[PDB]
Length: 150
Length: 152
Image (cartoon, rainbow over all chains, first blue to last red; front, side):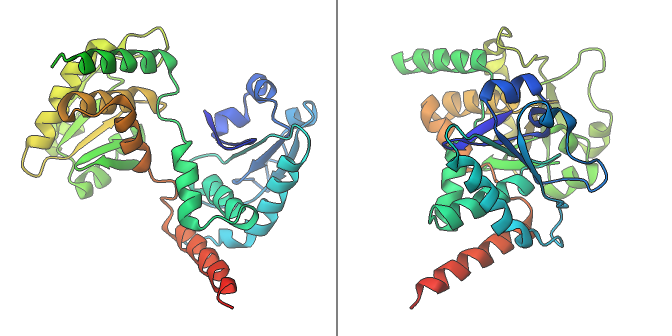
């Protein structure tokens, strides 16, 4: 999974970052990896895909200062959304903290949002039923209950 | 390893959370709704001794799978958990958000007369995006630094 939290700006997961057919379909031009491993280098396939990549080494822990990467990461994001047809995917390995943190800093630094506003923006665009069959079943439940079943 | 409390006493959470007895114990979880129950594995054995009551719904996260069939039974079970004094339920499946959130939404529609749209907003407004409390403090320090720049 990934969601579009801002035009061109996809917050998504590690499996997506690995899904070459999907990267390809969304037309991802850059990928920001918020759990880059010094060891496991940059991803091969990205070369053979035309994706520009930036890798932040961040550990998902309270002691880790992610602060040091806010400006760099925001500049990268801004450089990708600035290009004609630029689309970026921000993710890490596990948990939303590492990538969501860099998207929020970006919106504060480049779109003048307060932290409250930027959290609101991301949360409103973060999906909970990506399975479209389930959505349709929920819409049918909604229809029945509004006519007046109980 | 996450869960959000998206309605009072009602946690939307993940598989890791479902096998973490330290964490179940501390959050005070009394019921578990597993939207990806396996018939041939049966109920996690750790719940008998935690005193946790369980309902397993066998679902696949596929667009062809008909989850409609479980909306009432899951909704009843969630209603019973929440009606229990001190009751707290964790709703999860093994992967992806769809199976568990779909039942939470049907519950909000059936027991509280929310429209699908109202229930969707209620859940999205309560899923946290920065569980990491240090990162949240760092963002708050950035937010204050910008706000200060503004004073002047």
